[PDB]
Image (spheres, grey):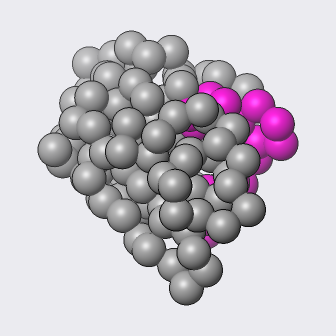
Amino acid sequence: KVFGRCELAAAMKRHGLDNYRGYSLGNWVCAAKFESNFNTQATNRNTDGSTDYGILQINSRWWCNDGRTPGSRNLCNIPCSALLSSDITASVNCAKKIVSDGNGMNAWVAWRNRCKGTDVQAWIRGCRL
């Protein structure tokens, strides 16, 4: 499923990400724009044994089990397939999870390189939220 940016803002709002650990809603929308282009189904497979999965691109060495990743900790306690759903819950309880431990929103290399200085409130200007 690919979302609209306003329709993912509002879902994310609903799933209480607006200001969790101090990160404006607005960053969370940016992080998934530049991590998967709003596609619930995205995967990037790496040389390294691991795969980034879903809309916020959560890796398999650390966060989910997909039974094929080397040094696995499955710290979200979810199968990675759980994160390619069209529904974004399993991925938001997993980003909340990542963001506790040592969060930056830094965990996500697109938020660091493309959302970190900007006006991220720009990704929610115009939505009803």
Which sits in the foreground, 23 or 81? Answer: 81
Q: Quadrant of residue 71?
A: bottom right
For the stretch drawn in magenta, what is the main secondary structure?
helix
Write the residue at 52% across / 55% down: 67
**Relative to 128, residue 110 above or below:** below
Which image quarter holds the C terminus? top left
| Left or right side of 2 for 15 | right
| Left or right side of 5 for 112 | right
Q: How far across and how far down the image is residue 64, in percent?
A: 56, 45
Span shown in magenta: 94-116
| Left or right side of 28 for 107 | right
Which sits in the foreground, 114 or 108? Answer: 108
Write the residue at 43% across / 29% down: 90
Residue 97 falls within the magenta-colored stretch: yes
- The answer to whether residue 111 is seen in the rendering is no
Q: How far across and how far down the image is residue 85, in percent?
A: 27, 37
Q: Can you name the residue that lies furthest to the bottom here?
A: 47
Write the residue at 18% across / 47% down: 2
- The answer to whether residue 38 is seen in the rendering is yes
Which sits in the foreground, 74 or 118? Answer: 74
